[PDB]
Image (cartoon, grey):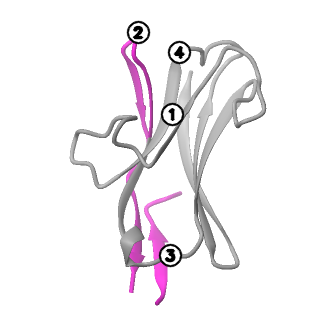
Amino acid sequence: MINITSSASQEGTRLNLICTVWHKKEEAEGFVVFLCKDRSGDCSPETSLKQLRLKRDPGIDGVGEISSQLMFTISQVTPLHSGTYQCCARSQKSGIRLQGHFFSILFTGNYTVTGLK
């Protein structure tokens, strides 16, 4: 395929939300990967928290060869970060859309991450 996966990592106070697209060499050209928060059906790169344009061959900003990764780093998790997140990718020209599983930050301060696996 070309497919998308979601993960997260935590270090000190920082929380990193990770969207990874797996793709054959060259297959990702024309794709954009983007992280959306609490968008009921208008998630796009323009309304995303962060995006990355993928490219035909490796570069030095998260575009790799058989996979590419977008990372969104939260310095410290506050109630502003509470809500539901989704990794997405699209190719405008192919009409391909890849959607990850919804996952949540729940701020209680202290927080949980749920819905990854």
Residue that label 3 marks: 77
Q: CA distance from mark 3 to mark 2?
A: 36 Å
Q: Quadrant of residue 53?
A: top right
Residue 107, magenta (yes or no): yes
Q: Amino acid at mark 1?
A: Val
What kind of element bears circle 3?
Answer: loop
What kind of element bears circle 2?
Answer: loop
Residue that label 1 marks: 33
Q: Residues within 10 Å of mark 2 (few under 14, many from 20)?
A: few
Q: Earlier in the sequence, mark 3 or mark 2?
A: 3
Q: Residues within 10 Å of mark 4 (few under 14, many from 20)?
A: some
Give me the residue at 47% from left, 81% from top.
Answer: 111
Residue 91 appears at what percent x and percent y? Answer: 44, 18
Vertically, is 26 above or below 7? above
Q: Earlier in the sequence, mark 4 or mark 3?
A: 4
Q: CA distance from mark 2 to mark 1?
A: 14 Å
Query: Is 81 displayed left or right of 28 in the figure?
Result: left
Q: Are marks 4 and 2 in contact (CB under 8 Å)?
A: yes
Q: Quadrant of the N terminus?
A: top right
Residue 65 appears at what percent x and percent y? Answer: 75, 24
Q: Are marks 3 and 2 in contact (CB under 8 Å)?
A: no
Give me the residue at 53% from left, 15% from top.
Answer: 30
Q: Amino acid at mark 2?
A: Lys
Q: CA distance from mark 4 to mark 1?
A: 10 Å
